[PDB]
Image 1 (cartoon, chains in turn brown, cyan, yellow, purple):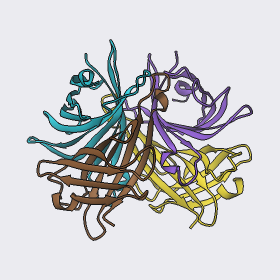
Image 2 (tube, chains in turn yellow, red, orange, purple):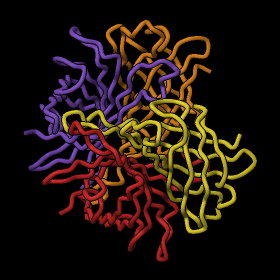
Image 3 (spheres, one colour):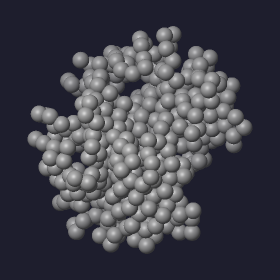
Image 4 (cartoon, chains in turn blue, yellow, brown, green):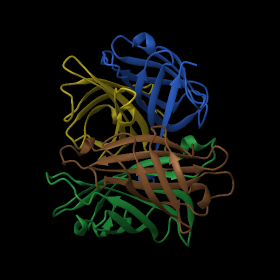
Amino acid sequence: DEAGITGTWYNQLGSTFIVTAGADGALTGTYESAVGNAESRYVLTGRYDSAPATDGSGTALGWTVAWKNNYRNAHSATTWSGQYVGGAQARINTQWLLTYGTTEANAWASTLVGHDTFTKV
Amino acid sequence: DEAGITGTWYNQLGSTFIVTAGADGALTGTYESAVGNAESRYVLTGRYDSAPATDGSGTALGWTVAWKNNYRNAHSATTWSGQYVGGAQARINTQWLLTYGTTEANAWASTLVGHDTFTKV
Amino acid sequence: DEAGITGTWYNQLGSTFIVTAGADGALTGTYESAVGNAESRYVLTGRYDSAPATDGSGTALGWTVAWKNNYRNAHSATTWSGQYVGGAQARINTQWLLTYGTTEANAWASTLVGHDTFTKV
Amino acid sequence: DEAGITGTWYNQLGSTFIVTAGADGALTGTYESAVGNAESRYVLTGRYDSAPATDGSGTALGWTVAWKNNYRNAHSATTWSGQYVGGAQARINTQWLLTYGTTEANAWASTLVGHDTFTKV
């Protein structure tokens, strides 16, 4: 799925995920969030299954963004875990975890959970 | 926290996380799970906040493993999202999402959630 | 939102959630899953905010199903946590956690996470 | 596990969970959080597997708290999903989802995730 994954994707919030899938299972690119304490692009890296099952299952992948770039530092990181589903209406269906740096006393409240669906349109 | 994070960490299951933290916010290394459909080491990559708050908050980070290497392919990826807490008893406290490639009909059941705490001992 | 919540709801899988909202914040009813190790109806209970904010925010609620009834026992429980959003296209937007009873050795793998959206149609 | 579950439990934050397990699978009681926008006791309800496996697996259960009582309204609900593990050092091991009522624009950020372990001591 190297060719299927590589490219520009967009989620239901309007965010823009720009990724390149390597032959070796790497994911590299940039993310730009339409919401939250974010502006412009941020580095991302991640990994995907480069030899998925051939039975119609999706392709497992994940990636991370730390929310620091030249413009802002939100002292936080998001990880997306999901699967690519190929075809005419290709999708990446994810669940994510956003952790903010906290004191020990506040660590119970450190982590948001949600779900993003990415399309090529 | 480049120096604090770089090194060999171990979780409550006995898994071994070997990471290098780059000046630029990168995390690279290897993971070896003590449980599940895994053997030997797997590539990891991720990101961390290279300019954390100085008020005692933790350092936000995350990373991914796709569970393919030369030995096995578990058609799955885990993402850990968490924070590094420095000091005498340093820790990485994480929550994780493990997604398995599924058919559309089974996608409701595609994703495990859990929590790992990493120590240097 | 007692009147808004009480009734029959349906999710994106085809499952059927039948609930009554009490003046006191209680939720009682039945759930019938279209997927998984389930047949027929199962008891549910839960709670909702009976005095929500008046600024356009949603109404927080949650509920549980243990997957035992007269037909089957899946040795598992799901909890849905979410919010009711009223209006012409009313919705309950949830995230859920499904825990299966495991041995200690398998407890790392005990919990699925996902997301269901309920509509009145 | 009716007798095993019924009673007063305490988590790693110092919160106090007071529950009664019914023969029919019901859980009823009160919760008092040591942290967050909470004071005093709040109603809880939930469900547990009243006929667990006899192979050493844990007992699946869950419960909800809406964070409204006579003192405060935090416009939020938590659901805990987990398993009871009996024996000399009995435990309830949970993962939880806390949803706050939000506008549509903020709904991406509506839900915290975490994990609580309850003991009888």
